[PDB]
Image: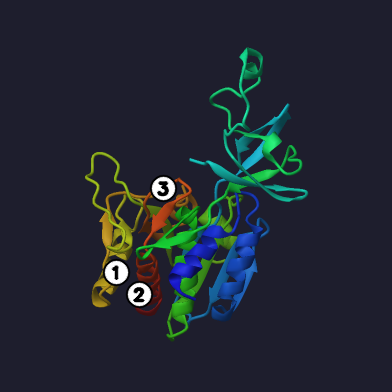
């Protein structure tokens, strides 16, 4: 489908850490027509496999979860939430989804006694007198946000991981046009995996020859000057963990195919621990995102598509 629509659908799905099944079920269905096979790990990660001519194995990785909260305590009319920023939340209960606003009290004229029962400033809570029916200890909540498009951008929750999922879905779609030499493994990792290599090996016992890890970025950390912009392209990480020679080969492919790129000295929000230990040459590439960690993260769908175009070209021309 259109990249903007794919991103809105990925953003709207709920897959808080530990409960990413529905998001994986959606990705499994959209990538099906573009892979030779797709396997799930025991933790719930999904690996799409697209056979090439067998010259080597290239692995692309992306996280899939989003923030969530669990009801840890129900005292009086206030339910306390603990993480597994946020204002509107939707909570999965035995009766369906209940919607509420973190820290909002139901209309009440407080007095010195009622004031004592109101949760302390730091606690995350919802006022149960505002719900339709119960909420119980153990119920899970996620941010209640409907994605939207504004001026060519997509705004919605969880794009810090879902935009990368969108890039990998588009790479598989684009690879259908080529007789690419590399065998490609696309990995959508859930929270409970040990690392990027552990997710991949939960499905295929292989050692990739090259790996590209997806991430998102925007602000630079001191001492660098902020310069990333939405729409100016995917951001090449140039930190000490990346294989700079593999990175230069990717840059040369982008140059030949007119893929506009941006760069950052380090990058990365580690996922590279296993890869480095196993000698996998790795590259970090990020999608520019604004309003990081809020319900209204914003990405440019063109950066997403251009990254997927570049990654499909890497599978065709690398080495």
Q: Nearer the viewer, residue 198 or 91?
A: 91
Q: Nearer the viewer, residue 184 or 105?
A: 105
The residue pinned by badge 2 equals 318
Give left or right: position of 26 versus 181: right
Q: Which of 187 and 200 is in front in this view?
A: 187
Instruction: Judge the density around disc 2: few (<14), some (14-19), many (≥20) Cα neighbours within 10 Å.
Output: some
Give left or right: position of 228 versus 172: left
Instruction: Judge the density around disc 3: few (<14), some (14-19), many (≥20) Cα neighbours within 10 Å.
Output: some
Disc sitting over residue 202 in the figure: none
Give left or right: position of 131 versus 53: right
Q: Measured from the top left, where is residue 54 in percent x and y?
A: 48, 80
- Asked if marks 1 and 2 touch (Cβ < 8 Å), the reply is yes
The residue pinned by badge 1 equals 249
Coloring scheme of the render? Answer: rainbow
Q: Earlier in the sequence, mark 1 or mark 3?
A: 1
Instruction: Judge the density around disc 1: few (<14), some (14-19), many (≥20) Cα neighbours within 10 Å.
Output: some
- Identify the secondary structure beneath mark 3: loop
- Identify the secondary structure beneath mark 1: helix
Q: Measured from the top left, where is residue 210 in percent x and y?
A: 42, 66
Q: Is residue 59 visible?
A: no
The residue pinned by badge 3 equals 292
- Identify the secondary structure beneath mark 2: loop
Residue in view at x 73 percent, y 26 percent: 76
Residue at mark 2 to residue at mark 3: CA–CA distance: 32 Å
Residue at mark 1 to residue at mark 3: CA–CA distance: 30 Å
Q: Earlier in the sequence, mark 1 or mark 2?
A: 1
Q: Can residue 223 be seen in this view?
A: yes
């Amino acid at each position: 489908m259109e990249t903007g629509k794919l991103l809105m659908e990925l953003s709207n799905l709920d897959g808080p850490s530990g409960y990413e099944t529905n998001v994986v079920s959606y990705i499994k269905s959209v990538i099906e027509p573009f892979v030779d096979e797709a396997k799930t790990t025991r933790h719930g990660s999904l690996i799409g496999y697209k056979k090439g001519k067998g010259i080597g194995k290239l692995a692309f990785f992306a996280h899939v979860d989003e923030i969530g909260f669990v009801v840890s305590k129900v005292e009086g009319q206030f339910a306390r939430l603990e993480p597994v920023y946020a204002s509107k939340v939707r909570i999965y209960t035995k009766n369906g989804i209940e919607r509420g606003v973190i820290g909002m009290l139901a209309p009440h004229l407080q007095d010195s006694e009622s004031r004592k029962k109101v949760p302390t400033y730091d606690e995350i809570f919802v006022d149960l007198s505002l719900c339709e029916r119960g909420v119980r200890v153990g119920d899970i909540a996620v941010i209640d946000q409907t994605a939207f498009e504004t001026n060519g951008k997509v705004v919605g929750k969880a794009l810090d991981n879902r935009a990368s999922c969108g890039v990998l879905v588009k790479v598989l779609e684009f690879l259908k046009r080529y007789d690419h030499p590399w065998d490609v493994y696309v990995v959508f990792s859930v929270q409970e995996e040990t690392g990027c290599l552990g997710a991949l090996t939960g499905a295929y016992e292989i050692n990739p020859d090259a790996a590209i890890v997806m991430d998102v970025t925007f602000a630079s950390e001191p001492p660098f000057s902020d310069h990333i912009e939405l729409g100016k392209g995917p951001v090449i990480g140039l930190g000490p963990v990346v294989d700079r020679n593999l990175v230069q080969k990717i840059i040369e492919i982008a140059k030949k195919h007119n893929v506009s790129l941006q760069e950052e000295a380090v990058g990365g929000r580690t996922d590279f621990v296993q890869l480095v230990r196993n000698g996998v040459r790795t590259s970090l590439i990020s999608i520019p995102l604004k309003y990081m960690h809020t319900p209204v993260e914003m990405v440019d769908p063109r950066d997403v598509e251009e990254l997927a175009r570049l990654l499909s070209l890497v599978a065709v021309e690398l080495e």
